Amino acid sequence: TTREKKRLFMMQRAERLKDPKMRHMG
Amino acid sequence: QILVGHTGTGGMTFSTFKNGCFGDPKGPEKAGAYRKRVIPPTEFRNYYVRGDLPLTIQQGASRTLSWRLNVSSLDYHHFLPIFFDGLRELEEPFIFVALQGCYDLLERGGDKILPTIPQLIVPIKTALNTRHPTVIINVLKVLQKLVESADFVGQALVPYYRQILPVFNLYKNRNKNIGDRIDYSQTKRQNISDLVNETLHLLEQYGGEDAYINIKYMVPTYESCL
Amino acid sequence: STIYNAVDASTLNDRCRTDLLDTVAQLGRHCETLPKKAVTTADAPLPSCTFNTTVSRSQKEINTYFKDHKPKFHGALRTQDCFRDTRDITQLSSKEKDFVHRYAEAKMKKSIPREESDDVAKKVATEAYTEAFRKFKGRDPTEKELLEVERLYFAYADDGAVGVVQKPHFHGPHMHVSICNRKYVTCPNQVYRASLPAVRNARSRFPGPIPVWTSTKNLHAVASNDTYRPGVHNVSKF
Amino acid sequence: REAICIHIGQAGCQVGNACWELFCLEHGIQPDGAMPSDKTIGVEDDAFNTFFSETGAGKHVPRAVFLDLEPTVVDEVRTGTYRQLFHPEQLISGKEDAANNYARGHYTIGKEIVDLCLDRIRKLADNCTGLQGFLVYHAVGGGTGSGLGALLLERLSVDYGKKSKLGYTVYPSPQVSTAVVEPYNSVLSTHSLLEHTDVAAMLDNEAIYDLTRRNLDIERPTYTNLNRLIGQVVSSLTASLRFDGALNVDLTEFQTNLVPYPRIHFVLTSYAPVISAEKAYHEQLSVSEISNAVFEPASMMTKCDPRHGKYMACCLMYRGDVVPKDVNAAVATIKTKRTIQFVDWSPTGFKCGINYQPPTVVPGGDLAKVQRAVCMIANSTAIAEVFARIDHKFDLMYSKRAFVHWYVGEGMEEGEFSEAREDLAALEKDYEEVGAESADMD
Amino acid sequence: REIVCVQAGQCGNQIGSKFWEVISDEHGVDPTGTYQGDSDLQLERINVYFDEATGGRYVPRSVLIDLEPGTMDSVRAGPYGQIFRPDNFIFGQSGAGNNWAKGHYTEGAELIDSVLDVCCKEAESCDCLQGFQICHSLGGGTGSGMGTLLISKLREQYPDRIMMTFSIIPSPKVSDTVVEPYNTTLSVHQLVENSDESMCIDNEALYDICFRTLKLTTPTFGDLNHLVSAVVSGVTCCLRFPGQLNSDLRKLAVNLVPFPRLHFFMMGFAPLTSRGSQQYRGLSVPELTQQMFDAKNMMQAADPRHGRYLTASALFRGRMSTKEVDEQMLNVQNKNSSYFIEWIPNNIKSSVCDIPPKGLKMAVTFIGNNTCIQEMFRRVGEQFTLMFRRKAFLHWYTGEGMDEMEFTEAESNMNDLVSEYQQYQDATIE
Ligand SMILES: Nc1nc2c(ncn2[C@@H]2O[C@H](COP(=O)(O)OP(=O)(O)OP(=O)(O)O)[C@@H](O)[C@H]2O)c(=O)[nH]1
Ligand SMILES: Nc1nc2c(ncn2[C@@H]2O[C@H](COP(=O)(O)OP(=O)(O)O)[C@@H](O)[C@H]2O)c(=O)[nH]1
Ligand SMILES: [Mg+2]
């Protein structure tokens, strides 16, 4: 389903960008 | 339109500024049934220009027709339908010849009118459908002359009421309401409704026993003459 | 929809319609009277390739009213002074002029006579100072002791006496604290005319740790700390 | 939501091989046209529609035509690994080349092949529901690329009308050269590109060779490296139509923001994190550093120095994990710089775009894998210097009519040389005049 | 007393999504539409924002409009997206291209009739209709053009109701688009004639709120849209809950607008504080009032200190004494007397409502009519004059069909608005 994949991608992106160092230079 | 400044109602809202249908408010289009329509070309014109009609116009002092032979001996099957076809002409001299020939043939036809009744239904039907008052008057007068022409003619027209009577209903009740004033249209017999009523009465009188039921079936607002 | 159509289609009576339309017209006229900024116009010597076109681009194209009421109250308190009116804030104060004269005298290593002025305020202040000095000490003040007039601020009392303001107040709004707190725009302790000081814009800097400020030349350009400081010169009255 | 690619001649077909290799690997389509279930998780769906259409059996086929006059590069495609991906009608080939003559391609030979090309493009355009432009790849140095590219752009401009046409064009480099007649073909090409293109992107092979020697660590580069860099740039610009993002950019808003006057449509292009895997562990790659990179002339893919002119508009495309506040801080720092100048009539000089899909890595590639990248297209008066260098070589050759008899024999009037040279001179003067600050009252 | 909301374009659709999340939370509506609340006070005014469909569920009276469906697929994918009525999403097939003329004349007129049909169907269903509420950006393309087109048509069809707009306008410092000045100037020209009350927001002011006051480490557009959703949901609180001194949108308009053109207002919401700092300072009516007038807490770049307040309004939510509200608002009027227009004896209206926003015991929202808004319009007009004198990008608009006279009319109307604010901003001793 498209909605499930979009929600999953957004959740993983939010998990990645939570660390400021990783947002800067990951 | 370009919106000009210092004219809008901005910041000015007031309770006093107050200013389920499957069709447009204007309603359906006027698909008129009384409108005139084009008259189809007739074979009377061709038979007159070719010269197959055994007749001539004698000028003398007034317009009459003379026949090169007695009309009791012509073939009515060939000639009677084509004169009825010319009843829907308008311009001269076709209309004069058509009416005079119809009257002369019906006047002294004899006992040979009866077999030709089934063949006259198509010109009668196609002349009345044109919604032109002059041809309607002419057809009604010819019909009145035809019913009284000979014996058993009226009884033969009863099964054909479904092809003649539809136009009769249109002008049945369209007479004039002038109150006290007298009517000058009676002298020349130019009133459609009076002709329609009197023709219906003639059709009933000569029709036999089953005339009234058929006319009532085709004209709903009818009353028995006898 | 225009205002005229709405007024004509409304349910108001005629008189109210006329009043509303007249109010709108008067507001429009008063707006026309105001100072404004001129509407921009395109330049005359503009180069080519602005009126030209291209085949693809050509294919794409489809082708009075506000009356003044100033009510006055009997016995209202005095809120003006002659001494306050004479002084101005953009120029040098009298004490600054005194220091300039003393600096010149020290530099030139000799006494320099002071300029003589015909201001009536100076004469009134000198007369009051001489009277006070004669009351305190039997002598009349000397020329050296009369230099004290320049260093002091003078004012009139309510009854017409001449005095000295010991502790002047700020010419902007300030606080007098008592059983209750109050703001005074003007107070008799003020020396200069009352005015509202200019302030710096709160949103001058970028929303972030980067050093970007708004430019001093226009309202949209930006600047940084390269060869000048843009944050100190963003003060404006409006 | 769809775009059709037209590849002409040798450079355009070879760049097409790299482009379609990348678009297949990025969407997950196998060389036989299938999409296995486990290669799709990781990216969303319908995204292929911009470049591929599926058959009722689920095979994918791409929206492209490959055009050449010699039967050689397309025979390599026909016999290579992707033979089954393309429909055989899309690979169109003639019998013989235009022999470096623009006149031979335009008048004599391209006129025979052009109607088959238009019929194939029509067959593609009938299978679309939201076509929003044509992308064209060609070189103006060769005969068929110049002549057939011009003839096809004229016919396309008459038949489709309003549809947008964006061109990626390789002009002859200022001192590296491959053929003697390059100036004549480039001059004759520029009139058609001026009239029949909405935005023109500039490339120079000498710039991509410098970029591959200095930034990448390749001592002996070849055309496949340059073509892979071009493919990455086109993928970055078209990513805004294909993947989710914070600030999307449709091609019409790009055209609206980048072109101030209808003839001033020639733009410079650059790409920031061109870097090798060995260099990648010594350096961080923040948004502000790559934004600073796209404005250095060592980053440009065209041999021009923007310090000799003024910028009119910039369009910055960011892809990957980026947050708008970092883009705003970077653009404000660039705007602060004193060696970057904008014309005073363009106060709001920047357009931004932000997309979440990071750039794809190709197995044999030389770029490192990175989480974010920025690509810039900008309009600047500095481009006038490239034309001036082409014009000097044209003037040197034309002073003695060095080769004109070839062009005149194949059907061209001698007058067209003088006409084309005067039109390019007027375009150079337009870029000189448009960049002059303000106006005087007298 | 029912409100109809309209959200246009991507910014409008995103703010609308956050607003409907906040409103659904306050009335205890499950994302399936089922009522799961815990007090009768929630049900008695649920009609104000929701219509009731049969078997318990509630659906929100909102119209979603955009020119490209990307945002609609995003809102349908959102956490509360299912609640929206499927027939209420209207969309086209190609974007606005950031062009005002494209959004207003060519693709606008094709869809506008379907939007007016849906808005009329929604309006005629209410037993008593209150004003409309519209969210859109002025710098965009479909937001500006179709928002102002729809505002004009609804003002023609419902002239006796209230028209209220919340609008975001491009920063001179943090812009995403080059042609922003034209779209902004034409939109302000349309609003000053069409609107009854207009609120303006700078993204720069919300970023300064987040960074200085909230100390957020990595802010996102969702936070910006929450600040906007908080003020919009706060203004209507007295319409839908009991209180000691009720207030209404029409009552706000009657007390705030002295003359019909001066209807542009500033907004603020007081209880803002970072999770680390909140343990060090308790909330109280003096603290909310002091933050409420602090320019750090105002959502525009123009500063009140460069102008004067004609009128202001404060709406308080929570259980509190009327004496503290009255004496605090008197103290603020007395202490800053130079910033209040002297020919109006008292400039502030107060209102008190018993039910606070969820998670706060008390809150206040501030609406202010201040002449410093003239600085924002002057800055936009300056950038327009730089671009217009040189014909910088006019061929796009002229190719769509615009007359240059439209540009000169819009410039003249904004210049007269700036002049009217400027006369009242400065003192006149005479
Ligand atoms: N970047 C790049 N440049 C190329 C490539 N192939 C050729 N060129 C350059 O383009 C110019 C030659 O143009 P061609 O494409 O060979 O000309 P053509 O289109 O084949 O025209 P004909 O020779 O008449 O068939 C030279 O400057 C080459 O350096 C390529 O694959 N990549
Ligand atoms: N606060 C806020 N601003 C937004 C949002 N989306 C876009 N913007 C801003 O609005 C402007 C773009 O306008 P846009 O909404 O795209 O116009 P449209 O294309 O007509 O809908 C830029 O300044 C964006 O930063 C959002 O969700 N919240
Ligand atoms: Mg070749």
Image: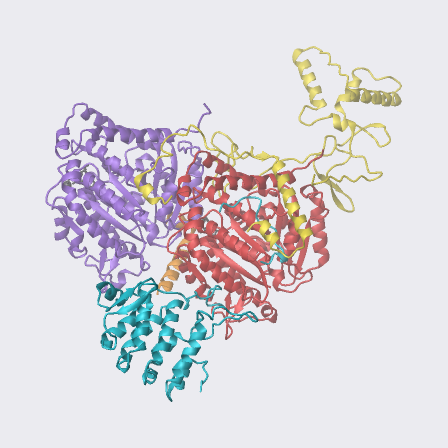
Chain colours: A orange, B cyan, C yellow, D purple, E red
> Which is more toward the observer, E319 or C133?
E319
Furthest residue toward front: B60
The quarter in which the N terminus of chain D is drawn is bottom left
> Is D257 drawn above or below residue B26 in the view shown?
above
> Which is more toward the observer, E152 or B56?
B56
Q: How many marks?
A: 0
Q: Is residue D133 visible?
A: yes
**Residue E271 appears at what percent x and percent y?**
59, 54
> Which is more toward the observer, E423 or E237?
E423
Residue shown at 45% from the left, 85% from the top: B224
Residue shown at 38% from the left, 70% from the top: B136
Q: Is residue E306 visible?
A: no
> Is B169 drawn above or below residue E96 in the view shown?
below
Furthest residue toward bottom: B209
**Residue A16 appears at what percent x and percent y?**
39, 55
The quarter of the picture where residue B141 lies is bottom left
D248 relative position to C167: left or right = left
**Residue E157 appears at what percent x and percent y?**
54, 57
The quarter of the picture where residue D329 lies is top left
The quarter in which the C terminus of chain D is drawn is top left
E226 relative position to D381: left or right = right
**Residue D354 appears at what percent x and percent y?**
39, 49
> Which is more toward the observer, C56 or D51?
C56
> Is D182 drawn above or below residue D63 in the view shown?
above
